[PDB]
Length: 150
Image 1 (cartoon, one colour):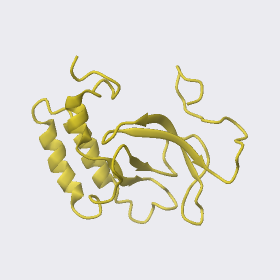
Image 2: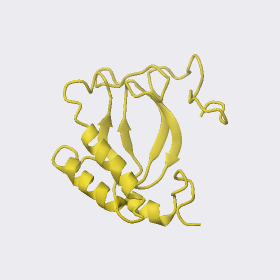
Image 3: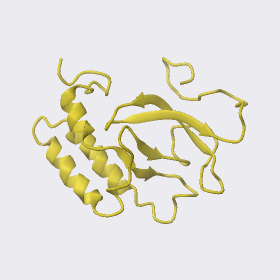
């Protein structure tokens, strides 16, 4: 096999290790009412995305992602994350389809993406934090031809 599994056909130890290098939740993705003043998140987002592309160190990939990693890991894009399998994307983040923005005194999150948890690799979750228990339309609104909702 090699480089063929559940991580877009790269869950294998080669891409999973070079992928496991770090997490993607050191970057806050467009929160909107929370994010709008500085928006300095694309630094770690670009560095880690490149590290995901480094995970494919067939030869140089690892080197591109490591240099990019430092590029962002500079100050406010390095020591801000959890143990693994996480990336920050809240509010104005095109994936939910739901309507809830969590911003402090406006803490109501709309984020329905997927159910994928790879330690040190990508993780997609479906969660809507709102004071309402029962959702008026659908339980989990994710646009996918093979799936019904989630």
